[PDB]
Image: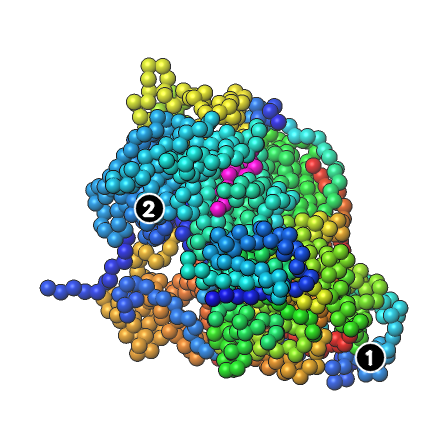
Amino acid sequence: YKLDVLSSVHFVPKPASTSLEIRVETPTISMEDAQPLYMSNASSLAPQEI
Amino acid sequence: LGESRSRQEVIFNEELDQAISILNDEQLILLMKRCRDWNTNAKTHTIAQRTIRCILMHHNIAKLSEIPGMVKIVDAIIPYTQRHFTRVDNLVEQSYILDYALVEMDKLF
Amino acid sequence: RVKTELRSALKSTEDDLGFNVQGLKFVKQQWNLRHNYEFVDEYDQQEKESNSARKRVFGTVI
Amino acid sequence: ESRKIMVPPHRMTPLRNSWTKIYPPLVEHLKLQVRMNLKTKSVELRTNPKGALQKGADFIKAFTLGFDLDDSIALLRLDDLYIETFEVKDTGDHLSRAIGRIAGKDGKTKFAIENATRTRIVLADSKIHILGGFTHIRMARESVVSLILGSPPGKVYGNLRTVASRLKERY
Amino acid sequence: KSDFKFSNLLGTVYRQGNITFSDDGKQLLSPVGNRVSVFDLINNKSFTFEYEHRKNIAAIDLNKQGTLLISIDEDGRAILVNFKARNVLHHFNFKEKCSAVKFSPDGRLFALASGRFLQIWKTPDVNKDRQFAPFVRHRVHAGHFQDITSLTWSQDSRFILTTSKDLSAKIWSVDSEEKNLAATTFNGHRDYVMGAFFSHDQEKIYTVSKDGAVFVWEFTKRKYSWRITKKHFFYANQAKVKCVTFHPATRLLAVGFTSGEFRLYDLPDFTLIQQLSMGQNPVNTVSVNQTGEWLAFGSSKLGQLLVYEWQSESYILKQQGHFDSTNSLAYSPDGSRVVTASEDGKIKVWDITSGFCLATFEEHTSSVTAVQFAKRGQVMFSSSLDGTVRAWDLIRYRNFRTFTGTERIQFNCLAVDPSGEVVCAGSLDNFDIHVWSVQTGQLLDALSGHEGPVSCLSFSQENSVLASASWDKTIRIWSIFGRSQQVEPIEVYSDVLALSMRPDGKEVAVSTLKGQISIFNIEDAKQVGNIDCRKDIISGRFNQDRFTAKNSERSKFFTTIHYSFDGMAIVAGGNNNSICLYDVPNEVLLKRFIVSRNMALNGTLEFLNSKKMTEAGSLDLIDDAGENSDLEDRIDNSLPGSQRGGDLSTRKMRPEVRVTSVQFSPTANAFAAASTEGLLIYSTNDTILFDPFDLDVDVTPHSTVEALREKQFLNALVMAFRLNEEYLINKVYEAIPIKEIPLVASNIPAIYLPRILKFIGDFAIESQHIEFNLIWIKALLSASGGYINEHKYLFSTAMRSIQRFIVRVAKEVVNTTTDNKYTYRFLVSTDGSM
Amino acid sequence: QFKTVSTRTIDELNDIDFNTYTSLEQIDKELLTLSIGPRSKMNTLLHLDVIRKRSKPKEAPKKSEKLPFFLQLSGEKSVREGIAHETPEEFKVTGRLGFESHFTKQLREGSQSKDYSSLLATLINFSPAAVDLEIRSLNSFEPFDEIVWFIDALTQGLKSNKNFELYETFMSLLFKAHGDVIHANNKNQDIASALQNWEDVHKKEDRLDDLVKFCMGVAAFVTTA
């Protein structure tokens, strides 16, 4: 972190990482920020993922 | 279903939907297993939707809930019905270019 | 004539589509209020729903 | 001008042992004079020359009804507090297990509806008394009437979660 | 056209100062840097005041009539604003750093803590005209020995209770006759007294200090002379109190510490009602609603703003902005929200009307360089310095695609297909352009041929030709699709940064480092025309540099340009504090906007005050950081040669003023500029500026309402169009009956067609007459919807504003009534028995 | 610059003299018209459970234990305008005649007078938590009067073509809260007739549907092609 900030963030990135992410299903209302409004009321998993 | 579309509350012939009304738990749960897996197409979905419709209007809803296994099926094929509803609603909203063409053809004279 | 018959067929199929959406989510919801569980506390409720959610694992790139 | 509140012979000994914390707000905060008739098993509240007699009557009537000492002091203070009484009346089948449905195992359903609706409930055999605000009494009473008239435990518990949230919410 | 005014300031919900609520606590007033934002939290909207302090503001108060605001900055330049008219009433310079300002509860006096003097002035009327000196001084009291940290008025506006850095607190009566009731001072704290409040009945006094003690003072006997009756302690060990407030009616003491933790207590018994954390940064502000139900907290380091109801344990809003670190913006394909790509590594989707962030996305592990929408607001692409382009579904909120190269480079700009099969991205260290398919994930191509870092990419929206432009002084046009693999290089005079592309794909406008904006015909690769812009650029002088703003070569060029959606204008911004817009037929400056007048930012002033230049260096390069009250800002952890890294503490210079991205609104006649202060949103409005269109002497509002009363509806509509007066157009529009909407809409002349379409858009977004507005839209589209199709770019922002009304209110209503119809049919058509 | 001046001539339609036009409430009784209020109230009503579930903090706050039970009611003496701080005004059902709420009393009085205008005015007035908390408590048990009074109140409401997105969400909130009891005693005569006349007025709402279908389809065709 401090080498990147010292280098004034011109750096060369980290090589590669095929990681592994678990996402639960939930409303995308609940995946949002705290404000009065919303943007989308879908579910985070597709029909072909359910 | 095709001959039901052909001729003419009831969606099949009435002897067929009373025959689907008088079937028990094991038969209706396997019928909804394969209505679930027919509903994943965009072609074979209408037969599945009308079989789900006649099950819903010829059986008892509390019975359908209390059958063990029919909450992992209806969770599986509610969102398919949702995307088919959005697709057919988009199709019927882009159906009004016929109406726009009619009003242009009427303003022609 | 094409407009009337085509839009009648399309509204006829989305009628039963919408019927089946509301009926199936009624069936699922009355099963839920029959025998889902008992949490009045919101934090234990949200942790219970997070433990009982549907998980799917995806191959991401970092 | 006076009031008489009859203490039943199942809430008599707690009144005597917690009496020394009952009469001080009755005789110096409220400026009444207070006697306890050991003959009629009653509490008499008279006014001295030097609208609070009804407040003292509700104080000792809450204690008489079955609400505890701090709950009765909460009724004596806290002007926006009310208390509603009703019998079940809606026998093995209906009377002997509707009250078991209000209670639950170790009274956990009663504890849950108390905490959810911000009332507190004393459940006799079939006599339900509820101490809370007006809207709070309304919601606790609607849920108690619900689970004596037959509702699923999932339905009444989801309604309890929702009523806790919407009663604490501004807007 | 060119008459833009400063509308809004998205981003940056809080910078520095105190949050205030309204009296009827519907809006909250938040000090952003030198503006003030007001967020209406019930009517979901927001505005920013147009006026501008010259330094960061430090104090806010408006009286409980809601009628006027006073804002003081961090060296005491107060500004009194009319809150309803939104115009500034007076500029008054108090001479030193004012810690707090408060109006009385009865509105008629205000007091403020300037240094170690409590001075009470009396409030000028809002109904009176502006005078040369509207404030009339009531008094100035001096009893503290060090600086006063807080004020508190009593419930009746009769006493005032002030707290100081000196370890006491004092009570002062307002008028001289009650001087004997209020002459005491309250000692006993080990540290700075952070607050001193009354109880509801003004009998108890609570005094809270920095070390963590709250003292209850009562007028008792041990005669009667204000004993201390109980000291309660917070016992937060490392952290200490940063902000205190007290709602006396609900007896609620709210206290925020320097560790993000805030506790709220029920005070005279000192029972912890709640304790929870904003974060890890200190809580700089606590403020409370008039009914005491909402608590607004502000932390100043991350720029975050909570308002939180403590009964129902829930956040009304938990927002956070970005100071100085915002690399890109993109309007949504309807102009409802703006997506912000920011240097701390995240995407933030800000609603424009309600000034808040809806979703945030943190999957980039470095500074996100570009965002761009595609598939008509369904998907959004971003490229960052960590080597990745990645795609975001804005329905399911999932990063579904990640594109890397093979060479481990960092991407600085991107461009997507219209028909979003292909994403494209260019770096500043690789000289190639990377071409990825979006359907599969693979690297489709690496286009080569630039001999300099590819500064900018854009796909033509109509014929889908790629235009890249790079620092080898060359714009280049790639025909990618369909067997061509065709390259056309156009040379230009200097090295290019910010290409932009016309909405019809005919021309491309490049910004160069000379200072010019050249405009080229794509198909016949020859220059159509250029604007020479380096002499209408405001390049200020930095504090550290030893060369004048005239001779500087820092910022006399535009690093971001953008076409208007009719193709006729270019907005442009750069590393300077002017954003300029031009009309490309005439190549002349329409208007230049000064993006900041904050002297706390660096490149604002062109001429620096020669008083501040001493015999050894300027006095603003002297770091007075060890004169600070505590260690966490006496600390210097700024590693030396860092420019544009992260974490503003790690750079040691003032934040320079710069605009990093400009974009026009796709629906309504505005533009957003990603400055360092936030997302500046400049918009016109038609309520002001009488600008007629070929009226004659017989065209008059009186004539229009006579034609309306005589019910020549088409003549009244075209008279109101020739007036171009918004109230008259609205009056005639609502007075035309439903029976003859299509006759009027068919007989509207073709020059008044974009006016009625853009009126119907900006009216129907918020108007309730949904079936009336849809009848008018249906009549206009049916009667004259061929003229629109053959004049696309005229009605390209008036038709996008109309289908911002159909899909965003009308389709939501239609969805609700559809679900009600189907739930009815189920609930009555089926079998519920047992 | 601070007020607005009248453009009315001196010598020696007050809205048109002050250059304003306060937009009239509904243009025609046969025209649908939304509420005069924020557009987001429909969405807040329809999804206020999941919005508040979003808005909860990630872990429970640290309270005390010697906290008073009636803390919400134990204020002092800026007054609270919620549904919880509501007092009754001035022989056992769910709400006696001394402990009737304002909503239930106005609903009963409108069922007497067959005019629910004051009921609907109170419904359009109060806040989403109050709306959910009033609809969720509606006596769905023995004779079903309060449900059917609410349903034909919404019928009288959306006959008037005003506030109709709010009357639509009130019907959605009814079907969501206790549409299971309506499905339970389906074929009950009073509740079936109340739903019947609600559908009789509500079936004339497809004017909005095919109007927005025309506008969407033709606007898309005209813009793209």
What chain letter is assigned to the residue under label 2? E
- Percent across and percent down for residue F15 are 30, 66
Where is D71 relative to E574, above or below?
below
**For the point 72% across and 66% down, which residue is it?**
D125
Residue under label 2: E157
Q: How is the image coloured?
A: rainbow
In terms of secondary structure, what is the magenta stretch mainly? strand
Q: In the current view of this chain or complex, which residue is farthest to the front?
A: D39
Q: Between residues F69 and F127, which one lies in front from this camera angle?
A: F69
Where is E38 relative to E365, above or below?
below
Where is B59 relative to F83, above or below?
below
What chain letter is assigned to the residue under label 1? B
- Percent across and percent down for residue E785 are 49, 68
- Percent across and percent down for residue E111 are 32, 40
Q: Quadrant of residue E593?
A: top left
Residue range of the region highlighted in magenta in the rendering: E251-262
Q: Can residue E521 be seen at all in this image of the molecule?
A: no
**For the point 74% across and 85% down, which residue is it?**
B8
Residue under label 1: B17
Q: In the current view of this chain or complex, which residue is farthest to the top?
A: E615
